Image (cartoon, coloured by chain):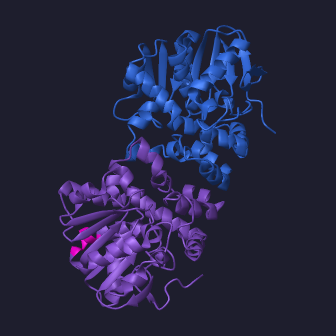
Chain colours: A purple, B blue
Amino acid sequence: LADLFPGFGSEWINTSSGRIFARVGGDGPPLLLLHGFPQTHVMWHRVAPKLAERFKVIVADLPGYGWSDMPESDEQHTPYTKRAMAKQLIEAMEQLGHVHFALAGHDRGARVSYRLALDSPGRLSKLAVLDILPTYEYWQRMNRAYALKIYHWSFLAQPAPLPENLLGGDPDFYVKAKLASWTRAGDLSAFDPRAVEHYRIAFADPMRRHVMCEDYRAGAYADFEHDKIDVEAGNKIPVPMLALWGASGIAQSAATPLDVWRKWASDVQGAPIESGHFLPEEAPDQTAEALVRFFSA
Amino acid sequence: DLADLFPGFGSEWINTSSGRIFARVGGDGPPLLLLHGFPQTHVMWHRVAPKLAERFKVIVADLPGYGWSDMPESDEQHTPYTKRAMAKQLIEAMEQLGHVHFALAGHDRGARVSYRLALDSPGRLSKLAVLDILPTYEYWQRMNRAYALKIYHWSFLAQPAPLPENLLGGDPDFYVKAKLASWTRAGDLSAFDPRAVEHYRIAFADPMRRHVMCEDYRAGAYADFEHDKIDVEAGNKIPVPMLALWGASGIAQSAATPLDVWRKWASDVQGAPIESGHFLPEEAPDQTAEALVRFFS
C-alpha cells in the first residue's frame, strides 16, 4: 500500500476501545480528519497536505476501519455507534494532548463528528461535516426515492451474517461499486488508484466488512435513537460548524442540507461543492479551500 | 432429486407469446390459478393445492421468469416482469387452457400479479385471494425507517444490475434460506417441507433466475408502483370479490390491518389473519386452505 501522506508521521493511539491508527502531520492547531465508508483515512490524502500547512492534522482511521483496531461489537453494535466512536476518538485525541480540537468528518466520520459535537461539544473548536445530514434525518426522509438511493442503509443494517455473507462472495466488486456510484462521474476516475487499493484492501478483510455492517446497524438503530433524542429534545450543536456537501452527493438528495443543519446546529455555515459524495477526492482544491477558510477564521 | 409435491397433478407447459408458463394442474371444477411469490416457486402451494383440488381445477403456476417458466428477455423498463405484463401473460396462459374466467389466489409476488390482474382485467376473475401483501404502492408510500429495514430487499433487489445479482451470487443458498427462514413465525426452515426448500434452493441457484427476481423487484420499485399510483389517483378499485389473508407475523399487520388498506383498493374484500409468518400456505396450510376453500366456494 502506498504512503499517500509524504511527510506525515504515523501513530497507533491506544484507547480503551483499541488503537486508532492515524497519520499526523503539520503543526498549528489540532484538526482531526475522519473518513467514512467504504474508505480509510487515506481519503484525505489530497486535502490533508494543504491543511497540514496550517494545522496539526490527524488523519485517523475510524474505530474498526482501516488499520484501527476492531472492538468486538455486541447486540447493540455499541462500539460502532457514533456515540461510542466519538468517545473513543476523544480518548485518542486526549492521548495526544488534544482536549480541544477542530474536527472534519466525511460520511460515517461526519456522523461521528456531529455526534461528538452533540455529546461533547466542549471538545471541539469548530466542526466540519462533509456530505451528510444527521442519521435521524436520513431515516426520517426514507421514502421510496430515498430508500432506493441509499438502499445500503437498510441492506447493510440487516442482521448478521446476511450482508456479510453477500459481501464476501466478491468484496472487490462492492467496494468499487460504492466508490464509483457515489461519485459525480459514476466511475473510479476521481480516486487516486493508490487510494482505491487502500479501500479495497481494507474491504477485503471479512472482519473489516463486518465492522462496516456493524456501523450501519448502529446507523439504523442506536445512532438513530441517539439523534432522535437530541432532535426531539431540541439539542443543537453549539460548536460553529461548516456543512459542505456535494452538489450531486448523497446529502442533497434527501433535502436542502443547510436547512436541515440549521435545525441541528446553532452556528452553521454551508456551501455546496460541485462534486459527488467524495468531496476531498472529487474536489480536493475546493474542499481544502473551504476547510482551510473555515478552520482559519 | 426434485420431489413431486403434487401427486396426481399433471404438469403443463403452457405456451404464451412471452414464453412458457409451467404449471401443475389437478382437480376438477371451476379453474383456480395459484401464483407463488419470492423466493419460491409453485411448489409452495403443495400443502394447500390438494385441498383446493378437491373442489377446483387448480392450476399451480410458476410466475413468468420463475421456477420452470421461461424467462422473457427483460428490458430497461423490466417490462415482462412488471405485474401488468405478468398478469397479461398469465391471462394468455389461462386462455390456452380455455379459462377466460377463473379464480385466483396469489402469494407475495404472485399476489401482486393477482391484484394487478384484477385492476387491469377484472372480468377475468370470479374471485381473488391475496396472501400476505398490500399493494406495491402502499409499501412504497408507507416507506419509512421501520419498513425500509423490514423489507430492505425491495430497495436492494431494485438496485441497477448487476449490483443485487453480484451480491446474491455471493451466497445464493444462504440468501434464499435466510429469506425463507426470516419471514416465518419460527425464524427457521422448520415450517417448510425440505423437498420444497430444495425446489426454492435450486431455482435460486440459477443466476438467470436470480436476475429475473431482481427484474421483478425493479419493476416493483418503478413500473409497478407507477401502475398502482394511476389506480390510486384515478380511484380505481378492484370490483372482484376478494379475500385478503395475512400472517399475524410477517409482511403486514401494522397500524391499520391489511383489510383496512385493501378496503381502499377493493370494493368487496374480506380478510382474516392467519397464525403464520409470511408463508401462509406452508406455515399455516390447514388454516390457509380452509379460508381459501371457504372463500372460493
Q: Is residue A125 above or below residue A176?
A: below
Quadrant of the image containing the C terminus of chain B: top right
Q: Is residue B246 visible?
A: no
Residue at (43, 27) in percent of width and height: B229
Query: Residue placed farthest to the right in the image?
Result: B1
Q: Position of residue B31 (x, y in %)?
A: 65, 11
Residue at (51, 42) in percent of width and height: B154
Q: Quadrant of residue B179?
A: top right
Name the magenta segment's main secondary structure. Answer: helix
Q: Is residue A117 magenta?
A: yes
Work out whether residue B81 or residue A72 is closer to the camera in this orientation and state it.
B81
Q: Is residue A242 above or below residue B246?
A: below
Is A65 on the left or on the right of B41, as rendered? Answer: left
Q: Is residue A1 magenta?
A: no
Quadrant of the image containing the N terminus of chain B: top right
Is A122 on the left or on the right of B205, as rendered? Answer: left
Q: Position of residue A48 (x, y in %)?
A: 41, 81
Q: Is residue A144 visible?
A: yes
Callout count:
0
Q: Position of residue A165 (x, y in %)?
A: 61, 58
Q: Is residue A110 above or below residue B2?
A: below
Work out whether residue A262 or residue B62 is closer to the camera in this orientation and state it.
A262
Highlighted range, magenta: A116-121
Q: Position of residue A94 (x, y in %)?
A: 31, 86
